[PDB]
Image 1: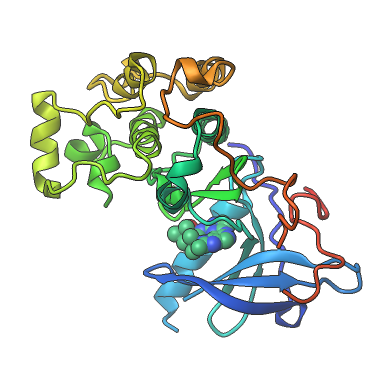
Image 2 (image 1 turned 135 degrees about the vertical axis):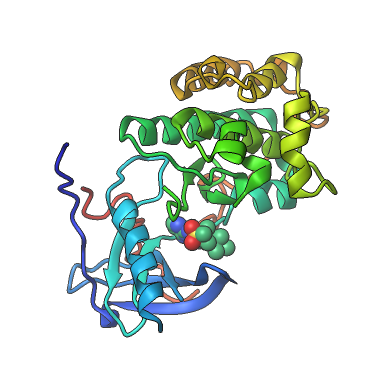
Length: 300
Ligand SMILES: Cc1nc2cnc(Nc3ccnc(NCC(C)(C)S(C)(=O)=O)n3)cc2n1C(C)C
């Protein structure tokens, strides 16, 4: 159908520097880095991904394809690739890491406004992916990255098996739709509302399918009013068409974000605060002089 005219930027190894390791797992190793292009007088904070088998290079390049094809404020985009012996993905630096660890590490300062705004942002990212006919297949709080506590983006399109985040049709029939992503969105919201609790803790992955067929779902988080929990529950209907659309989720959560204390009950809310550009030394190693974020540099 429509031709994909996305630009794949090839970047020189010499144009960027690795500073430290941010994470190292199955995906390979992710580094904090700086990208100093040609003679543009700019330093772009970046995240460098690297895993030498010919089978592995094919997988890192299929991920680069999807990641270079997206452009949305709530979706992680590929900045470029470096054609070294291994092959490196140059991505935007999300200084605060993944949302799962962020809600766990900062629960005592996470208020209703932040939780509800993150829900809007994730729904907006997902609705963009829907408009682009792209089905995520791995939406979880671990795959939502934090640029600033007030700005989150969806990542990991290396699937565009996590049973405990999957819709019933995905588990039993391997059916993946935008509606099956809505189920995963529901679990992601549950993870946030519980400040990073593990869904179905203790229960093995094979029992999940049987549990779901019975009618059993994730419990109501203590901070959740029936209004927020009803939305999570609607994301887990057997009939996929009965589940909300991401555009409905944008609207529903944003109505709630206008009067957040009416929808989430948190002890200490109002006296809670998270880092923001208002903070003295919010952006803080050596040279922080001509530094600019990827969202402001070049622009597609
Ligand atoms: C601790 C940490 N700090 C980060 C700063 N910036 C990014 N940048 C980006 C940008 C886009 N995608 C990704 N993906 C990283 C990933 C490990 C979640 S994955 C599975 O998608 O490769 N990272 C990733 C970061 N991390 C990872 C390892 C969770």
